[PDB]
Image (cartoon, rainbow, N blue to C red):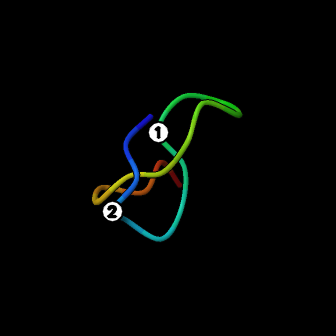
Amino acid sequence: CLGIGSCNDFAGCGYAVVCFW
């Protein structure tokens, strides 16, 4: 759910540094 990384945290919430593959 943060606004710094380039992928997704929790299904639609925002972005992540560790991307869930």
On-image quarter of the N terminus: top left
Which of the labelled discs sits on residue 17, or is there none? none
Count the marks: how many?
2
**Residue 18 in the image, given as x and y percentages of width and height:** 30, 55
Amino acid bearing label 2:
Ile
Q: Secondary structure at mark 2?
A: loop
Residue at the bottom extreme? 6
- Residue at left 33%, top 62%? 4
Q: Which residue is mark 2?
A: 4
Give the label, 1 or 2, closer to the camera: 2
- Residue at left 42%, top 57%? 19
Give the Cα separation between the discs numbered 1 and 2.
11 Å
Q: Is residue 8 above or below residue 6?
A: above
Q: Which residue is mark 1?
A: 9
Instruction: Left or right? Give the position of 7 relative to 4.
Output: right
Characterize the local packing of mark 2: few (<14), some (14-19) or many (20 or more) Cα atoms within 10 angstroms.
few
Instruction: Left or right? Give the position of 21 relative to 2.
Output: right
Among numbered discs 1 and 2, the one appearing first in the sequence: 2
Q: Are marks 1 and 2 in contact (CB under 8 Å)?
A: no
- Residue at left 47%, top 48%? 20
Q: Is residue 1 above or below residue 16?
A: above
Residue at the right extreme? 12
Residue at the front extreme? 3
Characterize the local packing of mark 1: few (<14), some (14-19) or many (20 or more) Cα atoms within 10 angstroms.
some
Q: Secondary structure at mark 1?
A: loop
Between residue 20 and residue 3, name the one nearer to us: 3
Amino acid bearing label 1:
Asp
**Residue 14 in the image, given as x and y percentages of width and height:** 55, 42
